[PDB]
Amino acid sequence: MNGTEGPNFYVPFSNKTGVVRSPFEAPQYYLAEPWQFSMLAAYMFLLIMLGFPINFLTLYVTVQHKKLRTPLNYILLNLAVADLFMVFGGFTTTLYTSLHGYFVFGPTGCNLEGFFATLGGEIALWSLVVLAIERYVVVCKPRFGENHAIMGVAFTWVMALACAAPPLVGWSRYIPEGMQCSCGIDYYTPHEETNNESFVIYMFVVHFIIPLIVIFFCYGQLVFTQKAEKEVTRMVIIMVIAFLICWLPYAGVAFYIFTHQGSDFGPIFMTIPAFFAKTSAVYNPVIYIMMNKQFRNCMVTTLC
Amino acid sequence: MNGTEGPNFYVPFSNKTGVVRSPFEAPQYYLAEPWQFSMLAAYMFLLIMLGFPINFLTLYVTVQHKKLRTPLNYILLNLAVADLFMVFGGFTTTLYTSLHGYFVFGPTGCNLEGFFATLGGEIALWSLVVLAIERYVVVCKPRFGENHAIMGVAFTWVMALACAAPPLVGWSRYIPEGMQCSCGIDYYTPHEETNNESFVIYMFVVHFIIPLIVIFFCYGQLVFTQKAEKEVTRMVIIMVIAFLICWLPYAGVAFYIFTHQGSDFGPIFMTIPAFFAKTSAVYNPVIYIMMNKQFRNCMVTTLC
Ligand SMILES: *[C@@H]1O[C@H](CO)[C@@H](O[C@@H]2O[C@H](CO)[C@@H](O)[C@H](O)[C@H]2NC(C)=O)[C@H](O)[C@H]1NC(C)=O
Ligand SMILES: *[C@@H]1O[C@H](CO)[C@@H](O[C@@H]2O[C@H](CO)[C@@H](O)[C@H](O)[C@H]2NC(C)=O)[C@H](O)[C@H]1NC(C)=O
Ligand SMILES: CCCCCCCC/C=C/CCCCCCCC(=O)OC[C@H](O)CO
Ligand SMILES: CCCCCCCC/C=C/CCCCCCCC(=O)OC[C@H](O)CO
Ligand SMILES: *C/C=C(C)/C=C\C=C(C)\C=C\C1=C(C)CCCC1(C)C
Ligand SMILES: *C/C=C(C)/C=C\C=C(C)\C=C\C1=C(C)CCCC1(C)C
Ligand SMILES: *[C@@H]1O[C@H](CO)[C@@H](O)[C@H](O)[C@H]1NC(C)=O
Ligand SMILES: *[C@@H]1O[C@H](CO)[C@@H](O)[C@H](O)[C@H]1NC(C)=O
């Protein structure tokens, strides 16, 4: 083992020189210089200050305008709510932690940071499953109305909770990653008390691979077989591409670590993909404004 | 108005073509195909056949083992009893009604179905209030013993009856919902003879908002402030999450209808949430077996 395992942490740094301290006890300056922690804090402050207004505006515009009741409108409203939980429930702890160089709030802080990021990302992924099904129904006509959209919304919360909640209560656990200022699922240690190995296989099969199979099955039908529907289909394509850009680096590094436990990697290895993935709280409403004329017009109408 | 109001019903279907009939007089096949009603009957048959043994077994094991006398054990015993009232007092009417496509038993059958489901759901909510307070006292030490647990049990019946009983005797009323095979509180009509509007405000304030405020106050004190106690605290978290998944869709759709009476919704709109919420009779013992090692071992000992 090239790192330092403690009771509830795995630091990617050798303790041969005796300098490692728990990320719940002391700033982690032995593994990165203070200016690097400051860069994480500046980044998180930007995400909060952009993320709160843009998601709140999306929520407000949608509720105000009764014409915005297609399945796409409902799904984007649901994403705005999930994004606001990411920002206030998790990112406020990411910022405080990065400011101090360690999880001042202890494991409770780590649970908040990991839980709300996992929940938000999985609501986004299962939302893309709902939209892929909706597009496949509408275009291929093998009708998806408001009732189906609302049922789809409730479905995304149930699937997302089935991924994000077990590590709070004894199946796997949330543990600090990278420079130790964010938390994720424990890919690092076997920790039989929490049955870590079976949770990770469950997560990658049920909450990554199966959703992507459905999305690409639906897309294969669309491709390998009016103007308003085209606009929606084009936007969903970009939402799926943006999701893969956002999360594939994190998913690949996580799976690498899981299959190479204790190997020689350092704190920067997981820091960059883990913090890049937090853009997930901001980008979907940006796509929305650029790619949906009706929503953009309503937003301009309300804001002006 | 987009639906059809009668003396004691509100059918979410227009009578502009003359086909609407009272759900106490004739099968409701004008608003849904016979196979849809058959899915409701099959679902209810499953809930009864699972619901009776799993709740009876929980009751039996608890009474047979004198070691199971913590506040959690008393509260789960109370839920098992309330669940059995839901299954035999209410769901037997849901099943018979769904088989025939209307309330063969008339308003009396509607009262049974609505009363026992409301009672069972409110016993669960007020039980979570009791557990939240017990966790707050136990963990934050601001002692919750056996006398307090039993007092809490009696309290949950009194509060639940203060919600479920008035619509039997002239404050609001039970009325069929959705495909007309379950009954709920009258969100649909003003019906001033039974003072409908004031009851709905009373129900949502006293019997939804106030309990939730207490639970999240206690949880917040938990978060911003041993192994055996941790297991109990984790189970209570999952009981609260499961309750919200089960009941929030129903509460949301009911409040939407109350504030948009006569609006253009169909029979499927309330059917799905109202029938999904009936899983409330089954799911708590399943959590118990999965998340309490002492109870699980006692059950295996009893069963084998
Ligand atoms: C890294 O190694 C150091 C040196 O062995 C550990 O610090 C010692 O910890 C023991 C047990 O807590 C104490 O009795 C010693 O006094 C400590 N020595 C010094 C110099 O502090 C340290 O705990 C290790 N870090 C981790 C995370 O395990
Ligand atoms: C829906 O409209 C039909 C047609 O008007 C109603 O049926 C009539 O009801 C009156 C009053 O009972 C009878 O005198 C007529 O003979 C009925 N006509 C037919 C063709 O059956 C029906 O009652 C309405 N449904 C509801 C629930 O109000
Ligand atoms: C469709 C658009 C997609 C756009 C996005 C494409 C992302 C491509 C990269 C993925 C990360 C894969 C991570 C694999 C990690 C292997 C690392 C490794 O072997 O490194 C050993 C070393 O010891 C470590 O410090
Ligand atoms: C903590 C975990 C929670 C998980 C569970 C989350 C549930 C989300 C569902 C909300 C239903 C709200 C209903 C709102 C009704 C809107 C109605 C509407 O706008 O359309 C009416 C139309 O007539 C239709 O046919
Ligand atoms: C900054 C904090 C983060 C990234 C914490 C946790 C994130 C996860 C456990 C992500 C899981 C995944 C998602 C959301 C979707 C793609 C695949 C996945 C299972 C790795
Ligand atoms: C299948 C039959 C049903 C769902 C009948 C009635 C249910 C209610 C009137 C439920 C009320 C509520 C409960 C129990 C808890 C959440 C809030 C609530 C007031 C909507
Ligand atoms: C630690 O790193 C060395 C060098 O890369 C490697 O040979 C060794 O296998 C690693 N330890 C583990 C447990 O993988
Ligand atoms: C019935 O539905 C139409 C179309 O949505 C709406 O304009 C009308 O206001 C509704 N009636 C009521 C009483 O809400």
Image (tube, coloured by chain):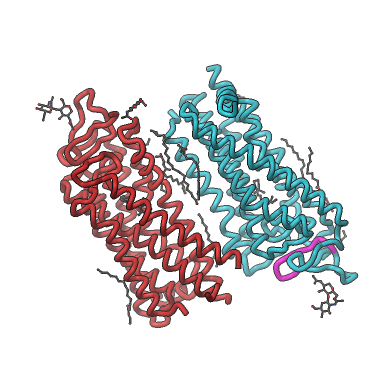
Chain colours: A cyan, B red
Q: Is residue A8 left or right of residue A58?
A: right
Residue A231 to residue A273: above or below: above
Residue B50 in percent (x, y) is at 35, 59
The stretch drawn in magenta includes residue A8: yes
Task: Please say if B202 is above or below A147.
Answer: below
Q: Name the residue furthest bottom.
A: B66
Q: Tell me, yes or no, if residue A220 can be seen here.
A: no
Return the x and y of residue A105 as percentages of the image width and height.
68, 63
Q: Is residue A222 above or below residue A28?
A: above
Task: Tell me the residue at 45%/30% (across/down).
Answer: A144
Looking at the rendering, in which quadrant would you find the N terminus of chain B?
top left
B118 or B285: which is nearer to us? B118
Q: Report whether B14 appears left or right of B124.
A: left
- In this view, which residue lies farthest toward the right? A17
Mark count: 0
| Residue B283 visible | yes
x%, y% of residue A57?
Answer: 59, 35
**Quadrant of residue B175 within the rendered picture:** top left
Residues rendered magenta in the picture = A6-13
For the C terminus of chain B, the quadrant is bottom left
**Figure quadrant of residue B124:** bottom left
| Picture coordinates of residue A153, whole percent (x, y) | 50, 41
